[PDB]
Amino acid sequence: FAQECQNLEVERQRRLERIKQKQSQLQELILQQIAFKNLVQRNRHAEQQASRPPPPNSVIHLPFIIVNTSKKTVIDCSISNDKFEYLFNFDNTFEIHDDIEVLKRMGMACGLESGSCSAEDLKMARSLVPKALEPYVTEMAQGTVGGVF
Amino acid sequence: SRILVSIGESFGTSEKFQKINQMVCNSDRVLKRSAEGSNPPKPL
Amino acid sequence: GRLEGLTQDLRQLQESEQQLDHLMNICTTQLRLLSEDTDSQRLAYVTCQDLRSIADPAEQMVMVIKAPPETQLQAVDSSENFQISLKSKQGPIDVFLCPEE
């Protein structure tokens, strides 16, 4: 049934690609869940310790984006009337980072991005995720996420 | 030499930002800006 | 034979994906609850000291962009310079620096 077998095998490969994409998405969503919840509890606790919430200007709410370049790098800004459109010119390398990426580098995801968890990091991570997602977190902690189940 | 992304994609953004960072990190053939020969914007 | 082999594979992959979808479902529901939660939103912020450990406003310049959802960001490598373009189809976009420099 070689003809039918060809049809099943492309279907199989098509599903293998969907699963692979979904596994990455699942991971990322778990890391966001952990990171957001971790940030929120860091701030909740820091607002107890010496009361008075932080001054508005010293604080950036999510979502946001970061752009960094050398302090020397010439930047040319152009803005539309309504501030809907912007254009920046750079005379040197710059970097763009997401808030999630910032949160990860702050250690909000408990090192889970790269399996770099201490016992306490992992415990923290496990407690910020519902029980059903625990086994997957364990998978992420070991790097044994692939093999494509 | 042209990467587009939407601020509203929980997937891809970071990796596409990192491809953006990849595209933009090597700066051998980049012209440096000169104060003379340019007409600076009106400081409002 | 191989036709049963592929059919058995298709069944494993169907069950696996059902499970994956379920977990993703649980996961995006957690994120939805977080986004509907007023107290969490109020507390979902970073300080200037936070942005430091990942790039401090002492040697490097740091720029914060806050565009509404759906807005487009174009990064360009020209023959001779670099550029970022932001186009928001609805709502204004906000840009600012960090205090320490």
Image (cartoon, rainbow, N blue to C red):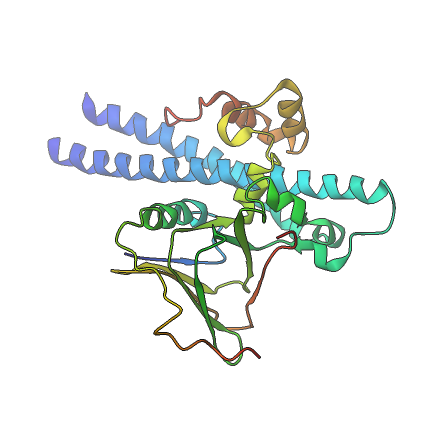
User: Given the current orientation, which residue lies at the most extreme left position?
Assistant: A2
Q: Residue at x 65, y 55 (%)?
A: C99
Residue A31: % across, % down:
55, 37
**Residue C26 appearing in the image:** no
Q: Residue at x 58, y 31 (%)?
A: A133
User: Given the current orientation, which residue lies at the most extreme front position?
Assistant: B36
Q: Residue at x 42, y 49 (%)?
A: B17
User: Given the current orientation, which residue lies at the most extreme top position?
Assistant: A119
Q: Quadrant of residue C79?
A: bottom left
Q: In what quadrant of the picture does the N terminus of chain C appear?
A: top left
Residue C22: % across, % down:
52, 38
Viewed as shown, does residue C48 lie left or right of A94?
Answer: right
Q: Is residue A91 above or below residue C28?
A: below
Q: Is residue A40 above or below residue C74?
A: above
Q: Residue at x 66, y 49 (%)?
A: C48
Residue C40: % across, % down:
72, 49
